[PDB]
Each structure stands twice: as C-alpha cells, then as structure tokens.
Image 1: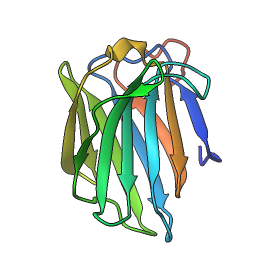
Image 2: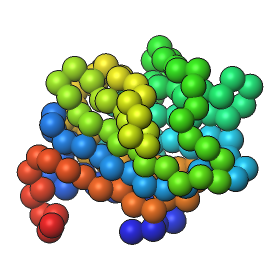
Image 3: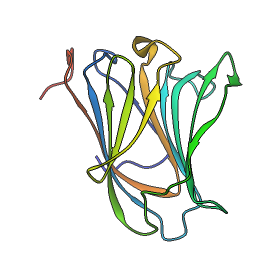
Length: 147
C-alpha cells in the first residue's frame, strides 16, 4: 500500500485465467520508462511470462516481451503512449484464455498472447520511473489473502 521500489508481490493463490491485476500509480515528471513483470519466481533473475515496458524516448511507445531461460524473445510493441509524465494512471491487466488484455485509464490498449503458461506466474514485479500506489488482485481463489 504505497510501497517503495522495486516492488515484488506474491500472487495469493497463484495466477489463473479470469483474474485481473489492478495497478494504480503515477508516472514521474521526468519518466523515461518503467515496467511490470508477471514473473515466475521470487528472485531477480526469474523468468518473466509478460513484460510490460512503457518507454519515453524517440518514438513514445510500449514494449512487450517474454523472458524464458534467461533469454528475451521476439519483442512486440505499440507506438503509442497511454501514460503521461507526472500524471496519475490506472493500469489494468485482465487474464483471458488467449492473452493478457491491457487497459490504461479505461482505454483498451493491447492484447499480449500467452507464451508461458499463465499458471507459472507467482509474482508481480514493478520498477522504474514511477510512484507505485497499489497493486490489487481480482477473481480466482485468494487462498491466504483476506478480503
């Protein structure tokens, strides 16, 4: 709840199709980039099923990729920037059978097809030029997380 950075949060009960990740934060006034990782492990070198990476340099854009066995795969990207320097934003990831759907501030933004099984994701990692306000989960079985 208004954590530091980097922020690593275990997903109570694991990640499953149907769930949603709700991120509230603020892009820094001097932001260059930041990322959200759907990681498969606690450690920093853990593989990443879905890497969401907004980049503010040259062509303002967002990069999407997967890291398996320490190797980044084919990079995907949308040459559009839904975030604004110094502005509060609402990032929502919905897990569907075929892909993660990204919605920024209510605006549908992208659909990243699954490369790594959704269920291998155990942690949500956030870091970069932003202020993190909160990370919330919706749907699925909460296991030990109270609500």
